[PDB]
Image (tube, rainbow over all chains, first blue to last red; front, top):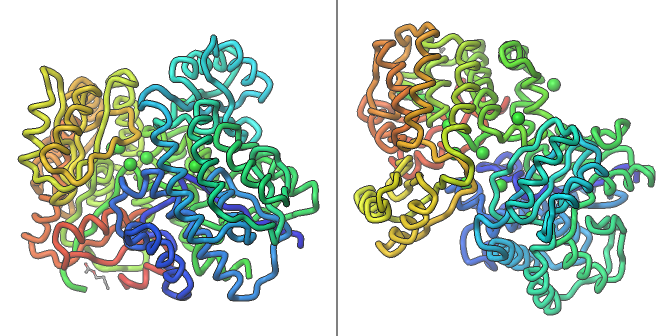
Length: 306
Length: 307
Ligand SMILES: CCCCOC(C)=O
Ligand SMILES: [Cl-]
Ligand SMILES: [Cl-]
Ligand SMILES: [Cl-]
Ligand SMILES: [Cl-]
Ligand SMILES: [Cl-]
Ligand SMILES: [Cl-]
Ligand SMILES: [Cl-]
Ligand SMILES: [Cl-]
Ligand SMILES: [Cl-]
């Protein structure tokens, strides 16, 4: 195949998502119904009606996004559409990729990502962590800025999203010091992100240790379609190593630009974003200028890509 | 159609890729964003379609992006010759969208205004000194009591009345955190800390509002062509100086959305149609007066529901 499918994460959710697709394909509401059975609440109703403040809490957003992406995947499979060459996803999206590749049972994945969200929220006391988007600065300069700012505390790049789009996170004061240094190094902008969880840095390690205990209780199978992991940019096939990659993913940076580059290096020419919004699609052509990127999350978009 | 109102969303309803479908089909959509871009000095449509999402989410960018989105849809609605609504209203930023659509404020001037509004809001208090919580399951008077008990001499107040049992509070960070605990002790079902730096719609915005007033003094406002119910007083104001004043008071006062929806029902409105990205306000209507839940309009297919 000359195309890949990628799955978005936190931030891509929207009240009303997938309404159009649900009207035409019963598998959408069926997928959400399965998710609701293991969550103990009506996930479809939350997604369609809100309250949005509840949908935006990570322990609800994660299963909402996982259900959304898996529902679209199920429509794709129902139509017997050609298989993608490889899958990948951004942070939560990696779980979506693993379900679609047959590694994790969907119902079990829904409970797993709900737990993942809970552990992330409970990881550090609110107000002690911070995240900043650094725009227009080379990865090497940002790494240096973080190293100099650290001064015994945690501060590191946590997302490599596109050339010139990098997110850093860690202890609040250290991140703030790093922002100043990035600006002094020439960054165009250093944007404080409204978030309490300093995701993907060493502060999440205790939470990862707890997540590891839960992964020991769930069966993972070999991937049916290759899945490129965020932590190592590897299409891992050993299920225990896939679990290890999820554990490490939690406290390690998301190497998204490399994931996309890896897809291109293999011969993929198009990335289909399977989930709400078009966030990842915006990154695709910034990473590899020749790649085509399209989002599929409604009847119109599904129809155009068939 | 039955007598209806159009309501406009605020901060949170933006999404990367919004209006792509509609922009492929009707020239006025990109024309509208191009007018905004002229004023802003950057390509707003490019930001909305490609990100960076972190830039789109900064309030001084989000506000013009949403204003442009809603006005774009309004222009398509008019081009297609769809029926006039009886009244308009919107949530916080959405009030500006309503005022442009009602012919009160010139679109390009409004774009400048909301960019400035966002900037002043961001600068109001140092980041880390304010907080905001969503409280679910308590009546307005219990929330007010929790905030008073929490204050300890600081500012903490309800800042949005979104539906019965859905209230947002904001103010000084510690005070707001105390208020969250007090709401739970009073029987709130949920007290959710929100990832937001700016404690909007409380007294901490008074200085920003004073500065916004200086700019409003330089923009021409005209009498509305369609009634607009304001968030601050729940009044269909027709005097443009009073509309300006309502915008300045709005900044440091609570958004009385529940009452806005009820007042629409009072004026004979049978349905509220949400006009902008997402379906956020559509869900609130359901929780205020069930029978006023109307169709949502923001993509090509949905224009059929209102034709
Ligand atoms: C055919 C719909 C456009 C009529 O104008 C109105 C309702 O003001
Ligand atoms: Cl989010
Ligand atoms: Cl929120
Ligand atoms: Cl995540
Ligand atoms: Cl900026
Ligand atoms: Cl697309
Ligand atoms: Cl807000
Ligand atoms: Cl937002
Ligand atoms: Cl375009
Ligand atoms: Cl606002």
